[PDB]
Picture 1 (cartoon, rainbow over the protein chains, first blue to last red):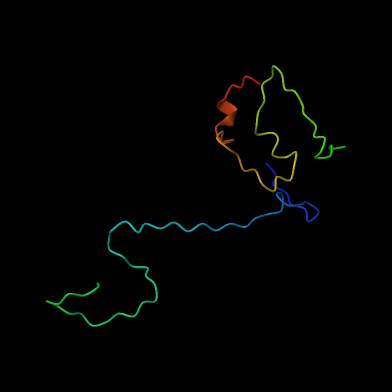
Picture 2 (cartoon, rainbow over the protein chains, first blue to last red):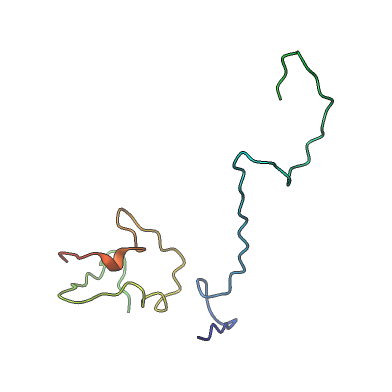
Length: 49
Length: 49
């Protein structure tokens, strides 16, 4: 049924465009990633991976 | 004629089926925060008063 909007409506009735981002950071092959610079890889030495 | 805060208006509710979902169009509802009782499943609760 109709969901009409009028500018004269007050708060709580004005349209509220909503975008919700769903993540799945569950340990699995990761693709979408942030802007962190990749460094060289080092073996047999204690590091903060 | 909403009463002033110093003399607030108390209203008795008696035997009735109160649907807490038709009141969303009665007020702008800037904030609908609620305490121990949640309005989500409120329509499934029976009150002494």
